[PDB]
Image (tube, coloured by chain):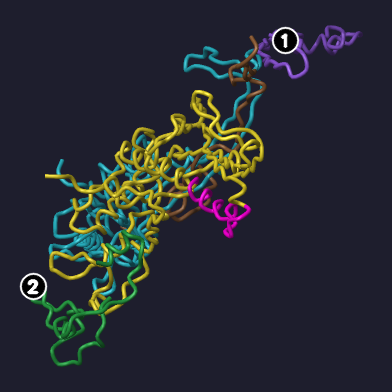
Chain colours: A yellow, B cyan, C green, D purple, E brown
Amino acid sequence: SLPDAYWVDGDTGLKQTTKNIWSNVFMTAEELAVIVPIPDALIADSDLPLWDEVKPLLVEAIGKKVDDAGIFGNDKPASWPAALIPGAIAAGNSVTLGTGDDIGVDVATLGEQLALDGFSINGFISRPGLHWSLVGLRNAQGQPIYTPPLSTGLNGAPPTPALYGFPLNEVTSGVWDADEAILLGADWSKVVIGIRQDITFDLFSEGVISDSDGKVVLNLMQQDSKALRVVFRVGFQVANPMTRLNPNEATRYPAGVIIPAGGG
Amino acid sequence: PLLVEAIGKKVDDAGIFGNDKPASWPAALIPGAIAAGNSVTLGTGDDIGVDVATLGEQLALDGFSINGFISRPGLHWSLVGLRNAQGQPIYTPPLSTGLNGAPPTPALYGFPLNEVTSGVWDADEAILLGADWSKVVIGIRQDITFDLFSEGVISDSDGKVVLNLMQQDSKALRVVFRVGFQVANPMTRLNPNEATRYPAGVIIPAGG
Amino acid sequence: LGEQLALDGFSINGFISRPGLHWSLVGLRNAQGQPIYTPPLSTGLNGAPPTPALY
Amino acid sequence: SLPDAYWVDGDTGLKQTTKNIWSNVFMTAEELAVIVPIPDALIADSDLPLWDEVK
Amino acid sequence: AGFANIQGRADLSDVHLPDQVIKDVLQTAPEASVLLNRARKVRMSSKKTKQPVLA
């Protein structure tokens, strides 16, 4: 909340009282992890150094799951808040593509909804291939719109990938769903990742891999084998403070999304 | 800091919109322009630029020249999203505008577009206010003053004690500020009629 | 075509094309009858066409 | 609760698991206070120091 | 019992499993006034001031 102040009815008028209120926000860590067993006869006689080769791909495979949970809400832990795209849709910070004349007016509609919530866009993330779909679209006059008129001719090189001077940042890791969104815009300072345990690798020469019902499937000592375990603990928060322009938590959100048009 | 902000909010709400205004103070800028007839309805012509030029002409007919605006939250992004009937950009020169390029500094006709980011702006009353800001004066009598109390009482309008700071184990912080407001409309050769001359003008929303 | 390669994760790097495509491009008019291979404001029938290229 | 321990059934007998449990206890602070009023005249007139006497 | 004793979060006290605190309040910065910055500023020294005007 905020306190008030009041006008006093002349000299020796009776002054009034006021108060102020605070509340809480929370963040919860969740765990993702995997194991890679290899028989050490194969480690010894493989020319390829298999433990140094697999680690970069495991680091990359961890990062892919965190994006998919935090942006799109897929496989999301039950304790995490709503993901950026479902949260922006529930708040009403959404724009259906081609409701205006031009994708630039739909992006501008996005900027205005955030400004009316009291936040400003400072960047995007977008679908794979968005840049070439921008060079490929036309005004109702049948001319290109992505560049100044004196640089619209098909012989010339396209510009650096951007909308309104912000880089497009196409999501090339394969996490994106183009049936859900084209573009997400946000104040990226309001999006927070809490590192509880950074990516740690452990290599084991002893013990077992076991089934759900307790059978041993691989014994590391008795079958001349090793296994690599990787673990990450991570929490996610999207932090909307109370702004002056929109007090209501149900409709104030620090991100907005452009979504695909509906079917016939 | 929240009490300094709450004081500044009440000054703007009295001087611009006239809500809960002191009786010794003159008419507030928005009700004052509306009473004088220095008013334009948004979308009376083909783009917001023609209504802004109508506001500029109305002040020139009173003998005053605009030197700046104050304006609704989110206006700049509604201007970059603006297209004519041929589907071209209105807000910047068509010969140098396309979707890759950064928007300009928020402005109309070369004047900064100061959006009011506090909660004061009632966008159901006005979109934009233009004025000669040299004619608007704030008089400071006593700067924001803070005093802390540990003895004494908060009392009712009828002399009854409502909180006793000593006997109920409590303190209180008092903030006080003293201020005057003037909008100065000298006689001009062009409009000697006090009832219709004014140094500010407003664009109001469409319809009722 | 440029978008389809980007949806596979490849970047378009150059072309090869049929005979006479360049003069097919300088003859390119939109449905409003304006040129497209060069911008309408800064090109008219008098001047030399550009060096043969595409994006 | 308290952890148990056990006798192992010979060399290479199978050892057993145990656990421990805790709960919370809560203490709330409460206030007691009184006021003693005295006239300035008595504080001035008194031959014995009235405040350091009452404490 | 011999087997499957394991330490759960439900076995520990609140003093074992505390929440971490951040002391910094989540808020936006206080907005400055319009008129106390746009209007011309004069220092008053009485409840009222007066000026002659040509009429």
Residue marked by disc 1: D4
Label 1 vs label 2, nearer the camera: 1
Callout 1, which amino acid?
Asp
* Placement of the C terminus of chain B among the 4 image quadrants: top left
Callout 2, which amino acid?
Gln
For residue C32, the mark is: 2
Q: Report which quarter residue B63 is drawn in.
A: bottom left
Closer to us: A161 or A112: A161
* Placement of the N terminus of chain B among the 4 image quadrants: top right
- The residue under the point 88% across, 11% down is D49
Q: Chain of mark 1?
A: D
Q: Secondary structure at mark 2?
A: loop
Q: Which residues are magenta?
A: A44-62
The CA distance from mark 1 to mark 2 is 91 Å
Report whether residue A5 is seen.
Answer: no
Q: Report which quarter residue A155 is drawn in.
A: bottom left
Closer to us: B28 or D52: D52
Please state if A214 lies on the left or on the right of B62 as rendered.
right
- The residue under the point 51% across, 31% down is A26
Expressed as whole percent of the image width and height from the top left, the position of residue A179 reads 26, 47
Please state if B117 lies on the left or on the right of C28 as rendered.
right
Crowd band around label 1 with a 10 angstrom C-alpha radius: few (<14), some (14–19), many (20+): few
Residue B180 sits inside the magenta stretch = no
